Length: 48
Length: 48
Image 1 (cartoon, each protein chain N blue to C red):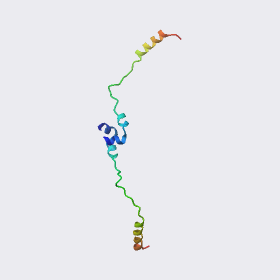
Image 2 (tube, rainbow over the protein chains, first blue to last red):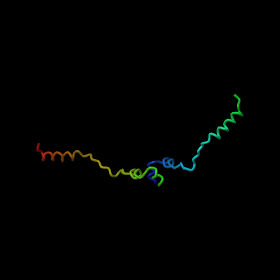
Image 3 (cartoon, each protein chain N blue to C red):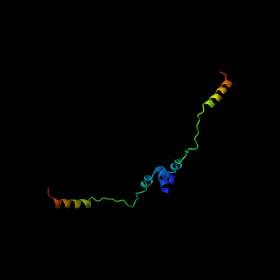
Image 4 (tube, helix red, strand yellow):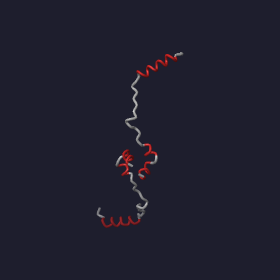
């Protein structure tokens, strides 16, 4: 492991560490909810 | 070391092993010796 590090360097092994996992995903399929809140904000704040 | 191997593969660490060492070098600076043996071989074997 010392020899492998000697060739590749310090940053390469540390940055190659895994990140992605299947449980952290977030899905936004709602327009219906966000469109309603979007309109009332316009309606109340109307100036121009 | 298992994670590092997982990324890079099996062949990469094995082929990257060191080879060169300063003590195995071989120097041929002699023409004077090799030219003499070269001529006598011609002289004896002359046909054409």
